[PDB]
Each structure stands twice: as C-alpha cells, then as structure tokens.
Length: 52
Length: 460
Length: 123
Ligand SMILES: *[C@@H]1O[C@H](CO)[C@@H](O[C@@H]2O[C@H](CO)[C@@H](O[C@@H]3O[C@H](CO[C@H]4O[C@H](CO)[C@@H](O)[C@H](O)[C@@H]4O)[C@@H](O)[C@H](O[C@H]4O[C@H](CO)[C@@H](O)[C@H](O)[C@@H]4O)[C@@H]3O)[C@H](O)[C@H]2NC(C)=O)[C@H](O)[C@H]1NC(C)=O
Ligand SMILES: *[C@@H]1O[C@H](CO)[C@@H](O[C@@H]2O[C@H](CO)[C@@H](O)[C@H](O)[C@H]2NC(C)=O)[C@H](O)[C@H]1NC(C)=O
Ligand SMILES: *[C@@H]1O[C@H](CO)[C@@H](O[C@@H]2O[C@H](CO)[C@@H](O)[C@H](O)[C@H]2NC(C)=O)[C@H](O)[C@H]1NC(C)=O
Ligand SMILES: *[C@@H]1O[C@H](CO)[C@@H](O[C@@H]2O[C@H](CO)[C@@H](O)[C@H](O)[C@H]2NC(C)=O)[C@H](O)[C@H]1NC(C)=O
Ligand SMILES: *[C@@H]1O[C@H](CO)[C@@H](O)[C@H](O)[C@H]1NC(C)=O
Ligand SMILES: *[C@@H]1O[C@H](CO)[C@@H](O)[C@H](O)[C@H]1NC(C)=O
Ligand SMILES: *[C@@H]1O[C@H](CO)[C@@H](O)[C@H](O)[C@H]1NC(C)=O
Ligand SMILES: *[C@@H]1O[C@H](CO)[C@@H](O)[C@H](O)[C@H]1NC(C)=O
Ligand SMILES: *[C@@H]1O[C@H](CO)[C@@H](O)[C@H](O)[C@H]1NC(C)=O
Ligand SMILES: *[C@@H]1O[C@H](CO)[C@@H](O)[C@H](O)[C@H]1NC(C)=O
Ligand SMILES: *[C@@H]1O[C@H](CO)[C@@H](O)[C@H](O)[C@H]1NC(C)=O
Ligand SMILES: *[C@@H]1O[C@H](CO)[C@@H](O)[C@H](O)[C@H]1NC(C)=O
Ligand SMILES: *[C@@H]1O[C@H](CO)[C@@H](O)[C@H](O)[C@H]1NC(C)=O
Ligand SMILES: *[C@@H]1O[C@H](CO)[C@@H](O)[C@H](O)[C@H]1NC(C)=O
Image: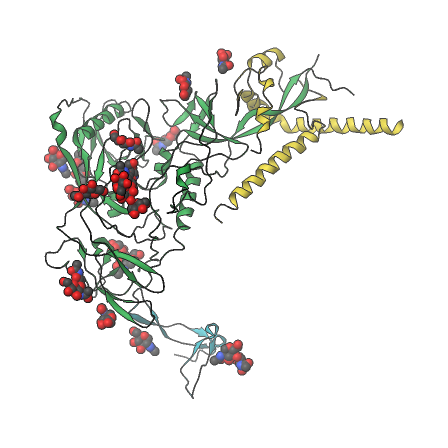
C-alpha cells in the first residue's frame, strides 16, 4: 500500500519462550539504519547497522 | 539576681531519626568454609558481652507498625539475596520442549519424566537427557489435546537463575547495632499491646538474636513471650489488617519425606552444571508434617480465652484460607535446602464459644495431626523482584524437628446480627515476621547540646 | 554509667555525668553505606564542635554566656527546675525557642570579641 519512502518493511524471525520454536515478526525500520550486506546482486537481504 | 543562659554539652535528650544499621554475628559463623549467605564476609563480628543498662523513671511511646528497622531489614535482606545469586548457574538452555510420561511402571502420580535434549560442553554436540521434575513446575503448552508436550514454568516470564550448591538457607541469628551517636530503646513491659507508652525503657547498643526465617501463615523458630499470650494489631476494627498472636508454650512440629536417588548432574556448557532430581528407589510416600493433638487443642483454647477479652459476647470460629492459588493459601517454609508448601485444613477446623474444656488424659498423646503436602522447586517469593530460582534437591531423606512461636490471623467480614465471626490464617507481605521479632526496639538519636538557667557570670 | 545514665535523674544530679555521654560520639554492598554513615557522624560531631566554638565555649563542657534570659521564655522558678525536673521535658518545652537563643549567644560573642580587640588595640 502506497510508496512509504525512506522506510522499509524488514520482516524477520525471532525466538519465542521455547529455544526450539521460532516465529516470524515484522516492523518498519528507517532507511539510514539498514545496510545492504551483499555477495551478489541480491535486493532483499538486509541487516541492522549496529550489529557490525 | 536574674536568669542568665549557659550552654551545656553532653546532654541526654532524644529525637527520632532514621539511619542505616550494622550487623553482628557470633564467632562460630566465621570459621565455616561454606561461606553461608549472609554472615561470613559482609557483616562485622561482635563482642561476646552484650552490655544492657536499665533506665530509671522514663516513659517512652512505642509504635511497632510505623518503624524504620523493619523496612531497612527487608531492603537489606532483598539486596543481599539478589547479590548472592549473581555468580551462580543460570538455567537459560532448559526452555526446550519436554516429552514427559509416567514415572516408569507404577507411576508416582506426582512427578513426570520429562526427557529432553541439551547442549553439552561442546557447542555443536547435543545429547538426550532425562530428569524427574515436579508437577507444579511443569506447564502444558498446547494447541490441541496433546499429552506429551510440556515446558518449564520460569522460561515464560523472567529468568531461571539457579541457586549455588554451596550456600545454605540455615537461619543463624543476627544482631542489629546502632551506629555512633545513636541508641536503641527497648521496652521490657510484659503487657505491651504494641502501641503506646512504656515505663521500663532500657538503652542497648545491639539487638538480641533474630532469626530471619522464611515462613508464611505460621511462625517458625523465634523468641517466646514472658507471661501470657499477646495480641498485636493496630486498629482491630476492619477486616483488612493482619493480627499477630504471640504464644507462650511451644508446640512440637516435624516434617518428613520419602527417599530419592541422588543429584543427577547435567551439563549445559563450560562449567555450568546443574543438579536435577534423579531416580526414586524404594516405595514412594507423601511428604507430611506432624503436630501434637492435645498441645494444639489447649493452645488454641488458651488463644480463645485470651482473645475473648477483646470480644465480650462473641464466639470465635476458624476455617480454611480465603481462596487463592498454591503460594498464598498454604503454610510455606524451607528445611535442609528444600521448600515445603503445606495445607492447613486440619489445624484451623474448630470454634470456641467461651466454655473451657479441660484435657486430662496421659494416654491420649498418641493421637497426632497430619498435614499432607507436595514439594515445589522453583520459588517466586518476595511478591516480585524475587530472582526466580531452581532449588537443587537433596539425596537422602530429611527431617524438620522444629518449634512454633506465633500465628498470623485475619478477621473475615461479617453480616448483620453476626455474633459468630471467623478468623482465617493468612500471610501476604514478608514484613510481618520481622515486625513480630522487632516489637521491643526503637532507634533513637541523642542531642548533646542544651541550655539551662543559673547564675553564672563569665569573667572579663 | 554508660549510655544515658541520668536520662531521667535529678536535674541537679544530672550535671555530674556529662562526660560519659560526650566521650562516646565517635566510637561493594556495604562499602558505601557504612562509609556514608561514618562521615555523617564525623560531620555531626564537627558541627557540634563548631557550634560550641562559635560563641566562645570550645573545650569547656559547661560554659557561661553574659546574655540574659527573657521572662517570656520560661517564667519558672529556678529551685524546682534544678531539683525536680528532667532534661526530656525541658527539651520538649524549650526546643521551639532555640534559634533566637543561638542568635543571642552569637551576638553576645561578637560584642565580647569586638570589645576584646578594641581593648587590645587601644593599649
Ligand atoms: C528451627 O529449629 C530447628 C532446630 O533448631 C532447625 O532444625 C535443624 O535444621 C538444620 C538445617 O536446617 C539441621 O542441620 C542438618 O542436619 C542434618 C542431619 O543432622 C544429623 O546428622 C549429622 C551428621 O550427618 C549430625 O552431625 C547431626 O548432629 C544430626 O545427628 C545434616 O545431614 C545436615 O547437613 C547438611 O548441611 C551441611 C552444612 O550445610 C552440609 O555440609 C551437608 O553436606 C548437608 O547438606 C544439616 O547439618 C539440624 O539437624 C536441625 N536440628 C535438629 C535437632 O534436627 C530448623 O532448621 C529451624 N528452622 C525451621 C524453618 O524449622
Ligand atoms: C561495517 O563497518 C565498517 C566500519 O568500521 C564499514 O566500513 C566502511 O563503511 C562505510 C559506510 O558505508 C563505507 O562507505 C566504506 O566503504 C567502508 N569501508 C571502509 C574501508 O571504510 C563496513 O562497510 C561495514 N560493513 C558493511 C557490510 O557495510
Ligand atoms: C525416563 O525416560 C528415559 C528414556 O525413555 C529412561 O531412561 C532409560 O531407562 C531404562 C531403564 O528402564 C534404560 O534401560 C535406558 O537405557 C534408559 N535410556 C536412556 C538413559 O537414554 C528413564 O528411566 C525414564 N525415567 C524413569 C524414572 O523411569
Ligand atoms: C505465561 O504467563 C502468563 C502470566 O504472565 C500466563 O497467564 C496466566 O497464568 C496463570 C497461571 O498459570 C493461569 O492461571 C491463567 O489462566 C493465565 N491466563 C490468564 C489470561 O490469566 C500464561 O498462561 C503463561 N503461558 C502459558 C503458555 O501458560
Ligand atoms: C525464520 O524462522 C522460521 C522458523 O519458524 C523459518 O521457518 C524461516 O524459514 C526463517 N526464515 C525466514 C526468512 O523467515
Ligand atoms: C524517678 O522520679 C521519681 C519522681 O520523684 C523519683 O521518686 C524516683 O526516685 C526517680 N528515680 C530515680 C532512679 O531517681
Ligand atoms: C532432541 O535432540 C535429539 C538429537 O539426538 C533428536 O533426536 C530429538 O528429536 C530432539 N527432540 C526431542 C524432543 O527429543
Ligand atoms: C524492667 O526490666 C528489667 C529487666 O531485667 C527488670 O529487672 C525490672 O524488674 C523491670 N522493671 C520493673 C518495674 O519490673
Ligand atoms: C482506625 O483507627 C482510627 C483511630 O484509632 C479510627 O478513627 C478509624 O476509624 C479506624 N479505622 C477503621 C476502619 O475503623
Ligand atoms: C468457613 O468458610 C466456608 C467457605 O465456604 C464456609 O462454608 C464455612 O461456613 C466457614 N466456617 C466454618 C466454621 O467452616
Ligand atoms: C486442603 O485440604 C482441604 C480438605 O482436606 C481441601 O478441600 C483443599 O482443596 C486443600 N487445599 C487447599 C489449597 O486448601
Ligand atoms: C473438622 O472437624 C469435624 C469434627 O471432628 C470433622 O467432622 C470434619 O471432617 C473436620 N474437617 C472439615 C474440613 O470440616
Ligand atoms: C530420615 O532421616 C533421619 C536423619 O536425618 C533418620 O534418623 C531417619 O531414620 C530417616 N527416616 C527413615 C524412614 O529412615
Ligand atoms: C522448641 O521446643 C523444643 C522442645 O519443646 C526445644 O528443645 C527447642 O529448643 C525449642 N526451639 C527453640 C528455638 O528454642
């Protein structure tokens, strides 16, 4: 829906109260907080900036 | 001629103030290499001669409900308890789903097997391990009628910090000493009702032996009274204020347990090993507490004939706790490093109408009262900020040859023309036990400056 | 007698025991609390000593000041004060008037010291 420039969706997965099961979540992270890690021309893999 | 003022230094006048206090422990508590949990490295030792001086003709008001040492003792106990679990094993790799069945052939109806997988000292290799977790520490996570998926209870809310298997929960006595420039006033009146003036005030530096026992709904080891049963309350009007009954004759109480195998050692990484419950050898029985019958009967009769002074034409009754979960409706304590939560249905089942009954039978002492109960292993005490533990089990059987000192009661709300009201036992906040053990003392500050009239003329 | 040996004794007999209640004013988790309490005790004693020395009564237990006592403060006969009363009721009914007494002692000390330096300079 819409364009919503300078923001990206950036849905991830995270652990629940069980260490085995994991569940998918979503957010809206800002553009300068997102760094494109890349080994090829992949336009979907992104990571958080401060984990580097 | 006329009055000229003169200044005096070293004057005995008093004020009320709130300052931090010290520790004092016996000399035998420092030679132990188990390091205890409180009095080995932090608290200072005391001299083996507590000097007490009685004052002549001073009357001082005492208010045990608006006190400072109760709150300071509670904060010191909470802080010292939270500081004693930091360098210990944390059970964070134990939230894996458990597959739990009956305890072999002929299940014990109280524990589940709960086999799982765990990470060993190597971060890649994983091994399948088993234990015997108690039923109140097992939560059925489910989406349908599944009877094989279970998990641990403290992974849901906050932390799994295990207690270290070197310290102990033995309640050795401690003494509180006032700092420099402060004193402690202690009231020696035997008919002290809790609030009001006292006429036998004595000044002391360090308090008497206080055992910080962990108990609710019933008081364990403590200081006895002097003459008779004493009632402690602040208003005795509403039904929301806890009343304390202080006894005179102790009643023997024991608590036992069947056998276990050993501490099964399970590793969850480098150095962090935890001791879970192993197997059970022999037949399984119940963990019960025994209390003498006739001693409890005439003790409750003495409480009735002493409590009838505050209610002239009303009969008293007792029944069960006023509803709730496991942690509040049961008398909870610990012994030997293992916790007990026990039902009090057969102790407060009776009434008194004012007519005394004498029990004169020497051969009737064989009859006892049994309290059947279960054992928990994860403790959520202090009603918050408790640092949720996992108490390690003990190998052999244990005994709890203890002593009883006081009771905690709470009146229920009556109806119209209700001449027969009830008294149900209840615990709640932790401050009541240490408030019952600190009724005598009050911290006081001395002001050495003063003025006085005389005929002194300073020479020029 | 140790702590508070004459906290309710005779007013005339409580003037023989000010030394023992003035001899003892200094005698991680808990590395800061006891330190703060001990420094607070030191400044309490130092404030008491400086307040004694500010009106020329340092190093002397019972010191005398030439400022008079007004009849609107106590209006009570000296004999039964010194033979019947105790210290605690005196602190109960005088402590609301202490600040102006301290100011009067300070002004009297200022006057005495100014006459002293005037006499020293004129000679
Ligand atoms: C209220 O008051 C009562 C009585 O004062 C207390 O009961 C005592 O409780 C303590 C612990 O809570 C008991 O101490 C334990 O005793 C066990 C059995 O003792 C017998 O066997 C030993 C030899 O093994 C003899 O020396 C002893 O005299 C007895 O004959 C011991 O096995 C325990 O050892 C454990 O602790 C030590 C030190 O921590 C460890 O090194 C050990 O490995 C082991 O883990 C322990 O010493 C004491 O015996 C009880 N008294 C009586 C008369 O039985 C209550 O605890 C107290 N509080 C409450 C809430 O009720
Ligand atoms: C991880 O952080 C380092 C910084 O320590 C990044 O290195 C530089 O980052 C800036 C910002 O994008 C680039 O313009 C430079 O080209 C980077 N290299 C150098 C040599 O300065 C590094 O890029 C970060 N990792 C990723 C995958 O972006
Ligand atoms: C809980 O389950 C485990 C595995 O199902 C049981 O461990 C087995 O016990 C039998 C003895 O009856 C051994 O022969 C097996 O070698 C064990 N398997 C292992 C250790 O992987 C365990 O006995 C069960 N608990 C109880 C109390 O019966
Ligand atoms: C995780 O914890 C919450 C509490 O923070 C649980 O919610 C309640 O827990 C009590 C205690 O067992 C139950 O009696 C209630 O029925 C629970 N629900 C409500 C709405 O109060 C929650 O159940 C826990 N998670 C799981 C899977 O049990
Ligand atoms: C995230 O974790 C889930 C676990 O439920 C997994 O199914 C999924 O493949 C993972 N990756 C992504 C990109 O969602
Ligand atoms: C306390 O005061 C009363 C009042 O006169 C007196 O009789 C009594 O002797 C005093 N006590 C002492 C120890 O001096
Ligand atoms: C645990 O890990 C083992 C690895 O040997 C695996 O076989 C098993 O399926 C896992 N899950 C459970 C619930 O045991
Ligand atoms: C006050 O308490 C002391 C404590 O030993 C006692 O000896 C004394 O008799 C008590 N005073 C009175 C008046 O009973
Ligand atoms: C509590 O006590 C005060 C005075 O002692 C009284 O006025 C008040 O009514 C009491 N509280 C209740 C609920 O009766
Ligand atoms: C105690 O409480 C129960 C709760 O239902 C009530 O039925 C009973 O009458 C009360 N009194 C006695 C003496 O059991
Ligand atoms: C205690 O015992 C009574 C009767 O034996 C029973 O009804 C009750 O469920 C038990 N448990 C609690 C928590 O009261
Ligand atoms: C209470 O005592 C009576 C009289 O012995 C008995 O019948 C009853 O079973 C006891 N327990 C309860 C929960 O009422
Ligand atoms: C329980 O342990 C005590 C010692 O702690 C021992 O005397 C007693 O015999 C044990 N109970 C049984 C049934 O063996
Ligand atoms: C409790 O009572 C028993 C016997 O009545 C006694 O041996 C024991 O010392 C008492 N407990 C305390 C802490 O005094």
